Length: 243
Image (cartoon, rainbow, N blue to C red; front, top):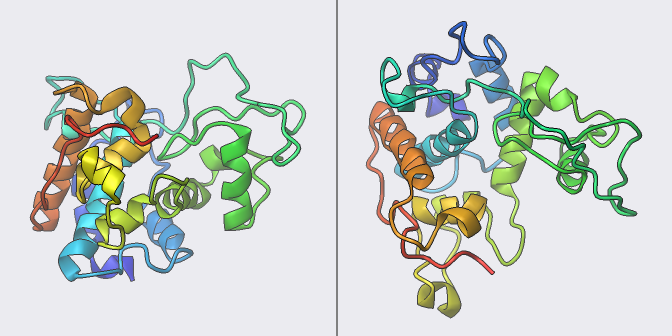
């Protein structure tokens, strides 16, 4: 199960400052909630080689650490020790509702960024809730008040494809192969393609980009704590975004 690959001690060393008083989400993200969330998704952190299993929870934690980071260049223990400092978007004005017959907005609810992957919009809360068995359309706020559904939404994102993009799971675990178009676009297996899946339209294909470098910094630090090599193709600086 995932606690066979990452211990409570490793998880706290990775998310070193999440419980400092300056972080909004102080005391929300617990190892226990992470473990409870992971066993709703067989396959997460238990597919492939033991090395790939370790690269998966490191990559998952790296990417969600960048979406919730509270670091700054001179932060204590470096900017890559400050992931998971936030649980919700906060500066948002919008309610992130796009009227939909498929995933209808609940009156008065707002679908701003919540949890580890900062899940946004009614058309993302809907399928996520359907998959984990809770009506997230009616109560999106559960993603910022219940830490295991918070983690489940993030793992759901990780495990689900969004065609033409593969799931992040499939590429880190070796269950995705680039088509001709992906290869022609420089999209080949590695951490870089996961960044491309998550935010490639903004971040990938235009040389060194600081947000991509932030993602990679957390990945490397988590890989070192887990004692696994990083694999190759860590950036997406010359990959075309998925289209």
